[PDB]
Amino acid sequence: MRRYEVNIVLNPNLDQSQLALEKEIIQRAAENYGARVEKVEELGLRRLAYPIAKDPQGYFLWYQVEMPEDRVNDLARELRIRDNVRRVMVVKSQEPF
């Protein structure tokens, strides 16, 4: 197991209902791939470095997870297939919470 930060950008135009659903899907996927979700932060709306799906902003979520290294790429791939997920970036945790 190793600790990673998962940075997720979502469609900025979601209702709180839809948003809550997307977070539930993310957590189930992480658990299905063996991750322990240690911390979740809702960062909120930011201007993207470049527009995605023609929208210049995105709703940001950040997770600190501990999970097997061999499954990290499969989880990122599973997350990127939801239509509301605009961007996923996973980095190794340097200064964990």
Image (cartoon, rainbow, N blue to C red):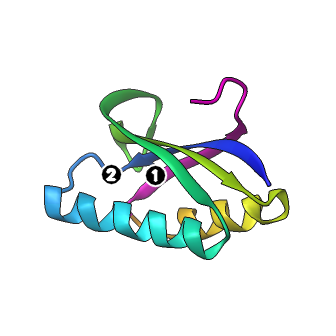
> Pointer 2: what residue?
11
Mark found first going from the N terminus, 1 or 2: 2
- The image quadrant that residue 6 belongs to is top right
C-alpha span from label 1 to label 2: 6 Å
Residue at the limit of the structure toward the right, as seen here: 70
Badge 1: few (under 14), some or many (20 or more) residues near its Cα, within 10 Å? many
Q: Nearer the viewer, residue 55 or 83?
A: 83
Please determine whether, in this image, residue 76 is positioned above or below residue 90.
Answer: below
Instruction: Please indicate whether residue 24 sits to the left or right of residue 2 in the image.
Output: left
Could you tell me if the residues under marks 1 and 2 are in contact, i.e. CB atoms within 8 Å? yes
Question: Residue 30, how many percent across, how many down?
Answer: 57, 65
- Residue that badge 1 annotates: 86
Residue 14 on the magenta segment: no
Q: In the image, is residue 14 above or below residue 40?
A: below
| SS under mark 2 | loop
Residue 14: horizontal and vertical position, in percent? Answer: 21, 55
Vertical placement of residue 95 versus 70, above or below:
above
Residues rendered magenta in the picture = 84-97
Q: Residue at x 36, y 67 (%)?
A: 24
Whether residue 32 is visible here, answered yes or no, is yes
Give, as a three-letter code, the residue at label 1. Answer: Arg
Pick the residue in front: 52 or 62: 62
Quadrant containing the N terminus in the rendered view? bottom right
- Position of the C terminus, as image quadrant, is top right
Report the amino acid beneath label 2.
Asn
- Residue 85 magenta-highlighted: yes
Identify the residue at image location x=61%, y=49%: 65
